Image (cartoon, rainbow over all chains, first blue to last red; front, side, top):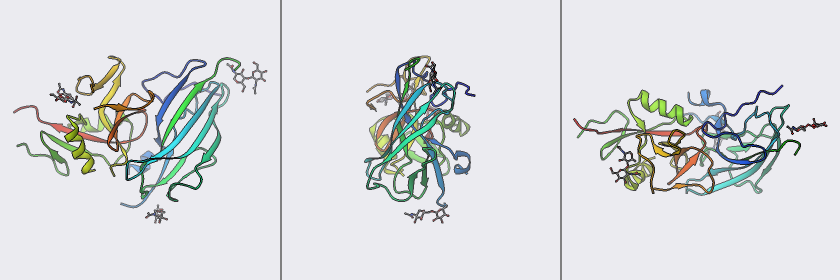
Length: 137
Length: 124
Ligand SMILES: *[C@@H]1O[C@H](CO)[C@@H](O[C@@H]2O[C@H](CO)[C@@H](O)[C@H](O)[C@H]2NC(C)=O)[C@H](O)[C@H]1NC(C)=O
Ligand SMILES: *[C@@H]1O[C@H](CO)[C@@H](O[C@@H]2O[C@H](CO)[C@@H](O)[C@H](O)[C@H]2NC(C)=O)[C@H](O)[C@H]1NC(C)=O
Ligand SMILES: *[C@@H]1O[C@H](CO[C@@H]2O[C@@H](C)[C@@H](O)[C@@H](O)[C@@H]2O)[C@@H](O)[C@H](O)[C@H]1NC(C)=O
């Protein structure tokens, strides 16, 4: 089962088959707990729709901003959507050697970015490109 | 000279509140309204640089500027259309604006960021 939804964008429609769309941002998955001095674990998610319920590909670039306004792209990520199944992570690539501290890492299971609030850089963000596929692509 | 609220920054004809809490642009807008304020309306580069020098500055902060679907144009929450301050971005990647470091960037409205509220003078 898959119920078509599009909440990762509030002012733009999803692309038509077979067009693409650029998405920039990140969700704070554990928002309710995190918005309540101590260093805490924040979990971030790319702007990726779990119930897109259409054959599509997601291709994103993950980055942070340093204390000297420099953007560090620490990794690449990919997801696929199907008309019959929810969105699944299909791959992660990390910049080697790791350009950041141990205070941020990407989870392998999901593509979730785990960060400690004591980090000497900004919250992670994803430059995602959503490409919806034509019928029988 | 108007008395500015407790733990609020003061600069020219404005009072500023920087949130420590992250949320969507709409939730950020609601929060400023509950405080009897509005999201940040940047007057000039001098106002911008004041905030940068007194803000943790590497993170993104929602401002009172978005791509309104009724007008089909970038507009400040005060109803004034946006002109060239420049919004940076190679592509159209969102309908909501935020101060990113020193630059003004477009981002997805459903994203989670901190925000700057403002209380401005409008007479006696
Ligand atoms: C979306 O992609 C799926 C593949 O994941 C397509 O399903 C295939 O459909 C053909 C018939 O058209 C079957 O012969 C295959 O067995 C199906 N593949 C799988 C793996 O289930 C589906 O047709 C695509 N949907 C659209 C609208 O094009
Ligand atoms: C709505 O907000 C905008 C942005 O803060 C105001 O625009 C400024 O207007 C002054 C003149 O009053 C100009 O000198 C500035 O350069 C403008 N700044 C920008 C960035 O546009 C505008 O005044 C406000 N409109 C109303 C009706 O109050
Ligand atoms: C940043 O924090 C790292 C781990 O944080 C830990 O988790 C929180 C929730 C608390 O339980 C805290 O006591 C833990 O330390 C540290 O390993 C690391 O040294 C810290 N980094 C800096 C730069 O201070």
